[PDB]
Amino acid sequence: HFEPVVTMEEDEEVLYKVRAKLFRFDADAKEWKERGTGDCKFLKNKKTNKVRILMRRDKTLKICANHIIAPEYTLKPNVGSDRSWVYACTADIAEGEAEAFTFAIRFGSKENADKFKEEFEKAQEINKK
Amino acid sequence: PQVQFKLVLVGDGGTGKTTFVKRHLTGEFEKKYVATLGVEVHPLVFHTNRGPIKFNVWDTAGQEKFGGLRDGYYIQAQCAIIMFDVTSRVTYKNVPNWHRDLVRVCENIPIVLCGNKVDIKDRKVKAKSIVFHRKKNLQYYDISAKSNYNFEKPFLWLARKLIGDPNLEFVAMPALAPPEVVMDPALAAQAEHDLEVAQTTALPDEDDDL
Amino acid sequence: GSMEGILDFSNDLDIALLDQVVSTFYQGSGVQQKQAQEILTKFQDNPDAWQKADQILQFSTNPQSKFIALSILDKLITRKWKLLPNDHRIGIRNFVVGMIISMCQDDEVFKTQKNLINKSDLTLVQILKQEWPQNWPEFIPELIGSSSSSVNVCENNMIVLKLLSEEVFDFSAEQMTQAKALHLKNSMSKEFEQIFKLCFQVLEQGSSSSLIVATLESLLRYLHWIPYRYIYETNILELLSTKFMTSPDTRAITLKCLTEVSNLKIPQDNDLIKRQTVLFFQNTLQQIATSVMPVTADLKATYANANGNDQSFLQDLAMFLTTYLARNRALLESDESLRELLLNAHQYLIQLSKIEERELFKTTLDYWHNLVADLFYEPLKKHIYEEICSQLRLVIIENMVRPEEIQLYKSEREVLVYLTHLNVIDTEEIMISKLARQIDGSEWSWHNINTLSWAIGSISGTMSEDTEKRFVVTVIKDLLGLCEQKRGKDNKAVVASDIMYVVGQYPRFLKAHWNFLRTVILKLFEFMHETHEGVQDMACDTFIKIVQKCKYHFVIQQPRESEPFIQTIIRDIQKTTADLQPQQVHTFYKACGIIISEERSVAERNRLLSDLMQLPNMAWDTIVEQSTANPTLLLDSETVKIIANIIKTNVAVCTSMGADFYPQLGHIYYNMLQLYRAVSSMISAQVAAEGLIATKTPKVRGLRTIKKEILKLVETYISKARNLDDVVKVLVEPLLNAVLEDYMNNVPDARDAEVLNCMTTVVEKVGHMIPQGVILILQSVFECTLDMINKDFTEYPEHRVEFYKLLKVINEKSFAAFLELPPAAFKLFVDAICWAFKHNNRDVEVNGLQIALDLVKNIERMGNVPFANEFHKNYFFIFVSETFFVLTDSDHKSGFSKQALLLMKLISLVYDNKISVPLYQEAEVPQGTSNQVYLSQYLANMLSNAFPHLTSEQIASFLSALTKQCKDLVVFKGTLRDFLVQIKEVGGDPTDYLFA
Amino acid sequence: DDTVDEMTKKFGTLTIHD
Ligand SMILES: Nc1nc2c(ncn2[C@@H]2O[C@H](COP(=O)(O)OP(=O)(O)OP(=O)(O)O)[C@@H](O)[C@H]2O)c(=O)[nH]1
Ligand SMILES: [Mg+2]
Ligand code: NA
């Protein structure tokens, strides 16, 4: 015998991965502010069957979106874009403690925006159960 | 948290020092030039395979009239970034001046030279010409706060020198399961108002890829 | 709160309160920190604060409070020193000197307070700049005398001398007048004999490391200016090259000194100095081999490990070796006994060149370029370096870079080309065997097959054609077999892409072998149907790249072909491009246009042109029938996309065909300009129905894309047009009518800056032929664009930039259009130029100053007529003072050269009497008075009011020199730079402006 | 010529699929 030489996403399944840019509306000023650009993922937890949005910035991998795709949310169009959605979120924990935001998420194409909307609604049906 | 390093950020007015930091803090790209008065201190954390690392970023003023304490900001700095603008020859001509004043206070610290704005078509300070860093042992990176080209590199390099591990990598911070908040009737009216205003305010940079 | 007490100067300064404020700033955080920062900034900016500085240096215990007190003193010494009474100057000097001596006496303070000591020294050096040697003749003798007693004082004196040397020789250019620079340089030079004698003694006796290192730090600074004699006629080279390389504290600094020694100005015809230059290199390399690492050491791994100062040391060794060998390698090349030294030094460089560090690799790559260039040209020199060169081929190839990293790739290609010439057999072998280790799998990866492909492609053209033929064939065969070997379309795609990358790089081979070229192109067409990421772009990018190089082979009828291959491409163009995205289709059409330009029979070129444009012309004809029959169909965004894509297809073909595109432009021109108008109306209708927000909507942005691509197509044709009669007679009148009014009469946010861009090109090429048209352009775009951009420097940035380009070219080509302006609009023209002066944006500033200069020339050119005389009376002093304003305000330093040139031109006009009128009005000066005397009077007054701290003498002398020197530009510039220093201080010497 | 024709034929069967 010769002796030999001596993130918290394990519990989830990826339903949808799309590349996107996320914005937060600064209500106090009159402008949108970028919050991050990366892969936006829809993660179904295997214990609770709960779907969430998880989005990380490229390179740094810092979390710029983290919330339940709640049944009450509604994806509205933005006046300036055919490849974006905007919605209210009552509790996002990307920074730390929960906080309300008015988000907008933009994609590479209209088709990616439309597929996102379909997936967002599929995830919403799952979170009603 | 307990392991934190003072970083001084210096360079001519308009080079994009504050824009660079804001991108690292919030993710935002600031289009407007609001000149820094003296200095602003911004805590900035990165998650690495060697635990978290915190930079206290002293973002200093490039304009002389708004210079403030000037080299008084450099005392006890443990690392630094010198910034210039590749569309502005004069900001590279002033790099030796910023470095002189930096090394007189901080004798032996890791320093990164950053040529910002490489996203711009008509580059003025050619790659060929950027050689000041060689004899001064500065690390050099072409960056762009706008396109994010190499925006992580300065902090990755300084992290490696300050921890003394060349294999240090940024890693994915832990994503906790988020809350299941039901919304009340009280906040609805103010959220409904902000949603109206947001829809009817165009997203910036609609010609970009994302 | 309580922290603001120190800003109350009516009472004594509470020092404990200062240290609260200072500690709260450095070691505190958040709201507390920010408030203290503003209080210290206001404390320091207080003009009386320096008076309370001696108090802080004595009574405060906080070193940050003392540092800040020295910064307040520094501020005073550089700016207001000469205004003080002479007792204050002696007093301040004494307690700066006293504090420094006191801190060096106390070993604990000397060890722990380096930052406060170094700041005090720098403050002392600012005093020397003012007072030495004229009012301090004994500074250097007395510095040397105090050095003999205390070792700590001796070390600190080396820090003081280092800083002095830096401030006089390295940093004086910007910060001092020429005269003061010269004075201080001569004064250092004059007493350097005594200073060196001390440095050398310290280096030879050599007790304390920190003293020795500080002395070597100071030596590094001396080497920038001292004469070579101090280095070669003493024993100091032996010490640097042997003693100080052995210990690691002194090694770092000594290596930098020897690098600068290798750059000294040396007599080139003296054997003793040549032997000494050989010897210090020999000694240095010997110490590296025995104290640091041998020639065989893996420096890649050492650098990667990043221990202590290993990376800095390896960088500095690279700098030393490259610097010295670039200058001196010839000294090592003829002597047999120096051969081993020469090759070992180069072997270190080979090892340093393997280090994974981009910027270091660039440093070493610059040297390899210098070497291999010399071995290509210098007789009998390549046989020496055969083994170094063979290793370098592996190094360059293994570190080859994507052509995208422009600069790096060129430097690498050039070196690898030189090395291929020097030994073509060796280069082939290394590439073929590296390629074999991709097939066997030992070196296999996506990145590794990519790098080898880029390397193999870089040496195209260097081999003989016959060798190239065998080489290419072997490489393509091997790569083809590599693709068949691999599995999964991820892997197959990487190799196929590299296969096609390499063939694209060898056009000489493609030209000689038609069958093969045809197969390559038909294969690229098969790849245009692949959906897998990257493949379609690579297929299209390769196609146009091959076509740019091989044009002629597509346009002639090859042997054993029924037609020129261009015809075969055009026939199947729908089927070939069916799966491509629009921008990919446009590259394809542009590629076809490159080929069509080769056919020089006109009837046949035009026939191919309309054949190529058949699909978009039929899409076009149907859309013009649809949208004119009823404007409702244009509201559909799918129709907007299709239209924009037809226009872009025309832009793509016009880009490569230029003057040849004319018959196609004629097919669409009139209907296209009608389309511009219909689209313009929809944009205005949406903006009226929805508001300014409309301009952000996808609908309206789509419509604006149509207008912009139409403007781009016309700009593109006119820029390359050979028949300018047709441009005037046929294109221009319809264009101006379509675009000018629409621009003028839309709200600012709906105006396209591309209108301005398009007009610039029109004026550029045909402005001379359309004076009435140029007038019409100005009327329509000038005043309304100026009102958009004259409220701030930020808004409408594209319009801002194109505006001054348009005015620039109008001012060059059709100056007569400005003469026809009503005097009030001519005044807005002058206001606009001066407005450009004040921009930071370089595109605007540079054109601003250029327009000003060309305008002055245009007015001079008119000679003695009323318009030129009314221009000088109204605007000459406006231009002089506005140019002076941006020279002196510290916010337009980027424009200094062009400011100076304009100012010189303005002053020369008066000095040469080229203005034929009184620049003064009636009853303001005596009647016989020349403009020269009135120019001096006005400028004296102007500068006196603008810089009231300058003496009348200062201003009189500056202007006296400035006007003398208005022919010699470099001297004029020097005088201006002297003035920019003097305005930052009080009591500047007026004699400084006699510098020559 | 001979070697180039052999190479050309192999080129024609290049693929991304197995
Ligand atoms: N194109 C481009 N613009 C940039 C980039 N980074 C910053 N800018 C712009 O440059 C301008 C100046 O940026 P700041 O961050 O205010 O400059 P600063 O260095 O903080 O200046 P001071 O604080 O006065 O010293 C801002 O308008 C930025 O939007 C970049 O990467 N690309
Ligand atoms: Mg700033
Ligand atoms: Na190549």
Image (cartoon, coloured by chain):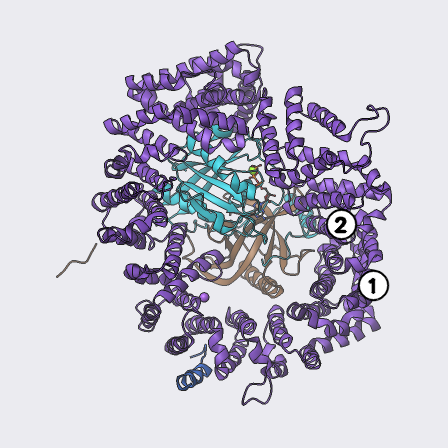
Chain colours: A brown, B cyan, C purple, D blue
Q: Taking B102 as reference, is C445 left or right?
A: left
**Mark 2 touching mark 1, by CB under 8 A?**
no
**Which quadrant of the structure image shows residue A100?**
top right
Vertical position of residue C454 compared to residue B123: above or below = below
**Residue C206 in view of the camera:** no
Towards the viewer: C365 or C38 = C365
Chain where mark 1 sits: C
Q: Please report the residue visible at 84 percent of the width from the left and 73 percent of the height from the top.
A: C629
Q: Taking C493 as reference, is C684 left or right?
A: right
**Residue C655 in view of the camera:** yes
Vertical position of residue C464 compared to residue C752: above or below = below
Residue C733's label in the rendered image is 1
- Foreground label between 2 and 1: 2
Determine the secondary structure under disc 2.
helix
* Sooner in the amino-acid sequence: mark 2 or mark 1: 1
Towards the viewer: C740 or C56 = C740
How far from the left and from the top, in percent, is residue C575? 60, 81
Residue hosting label 2: C811
Q: Residue furthest left?
A: A1
Q: Please report the residue visible at 30 percent of the width from the left and 41 percent of the height from the top.
A: C273
Type of amino acid under label 1: Glu
Q: Taking C229 as reference, is C977 left or right?
A: right
Cα–Cα span, label 2 and label 1:
21 Å
Determine the secondary structure under disc 1.
helix
Q: Taking C203 as reference, is C406 left or right?
A: right
Q: Please report the residue visible at 49 percent of the width from the left and 43 percent of the height from the top.
A: A96
Type of amino acid under label 2: Asn
Chain where mark 2 sits: C
Q: Quadrant of the C terminus of chain B?
A: bottom right
